[PDB]
Length: 283
Length: 9
View (spheres, rainbow over the protein chains, first blue to last red):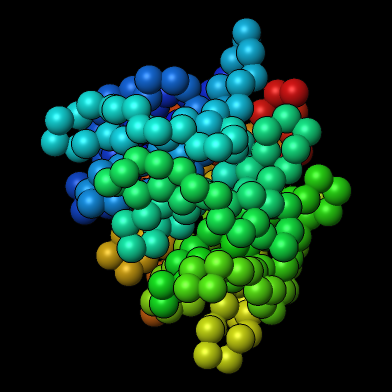
């Protein structure tokens, strides 16, 4: 099902709320040990991981270097080794088991650093950093390659995207998106990299566009109904779900669904409560 | 509130 961990509405949240569009409604599960927003969700071996973020509370604002797994049979969280640095507004992209932690911020410092960690040695090792410092970065994996998409460098919000070549441990700039997007929702559907919504420094976005690898072009697809940045995103059996986010005024509970074969974005259902900055994955 | 995430400073 579609799980969402963390988020923010007045303070960082511990929530965990699996959803099933074939079930129709939601389900509440084990709370995160430490509240988190600006985190990323990913599944490795059915094991739902929660990476980086921060706890923005009435008594603090602690950037999280933590990594935490939730076995969905046992319903219990478990602390795994911590990253080299805290990463608020992180991106992550699963790659043959090993988890990739991308960019993010710690205080004033916008990372270009990247580090990996797999469920075996439970260690973090720094790899080549990105060409760009990126927080609010969207991350995707296509043909066993890692794409970092959009984000914010401290001063400029980005339309650029860059690709990590593991066998060479270097980053290469690719064709930029048509739109500057920080805090967008980025995922692979079919074999295109999708990039939905985000913020360009003036306005939240409802536009969506997708990247075709063979032609290296970013085609503009159907836009969503409600502009949103800091949204969750995931693909559930060949369709796209965006959950929550911020539109400059409101913390959204709206969940829209994109149907590719018709190119239409419909609002299937909403969340139990509006929130931004969640981690989303599927297992 | 953060223009992008809405979170407080």
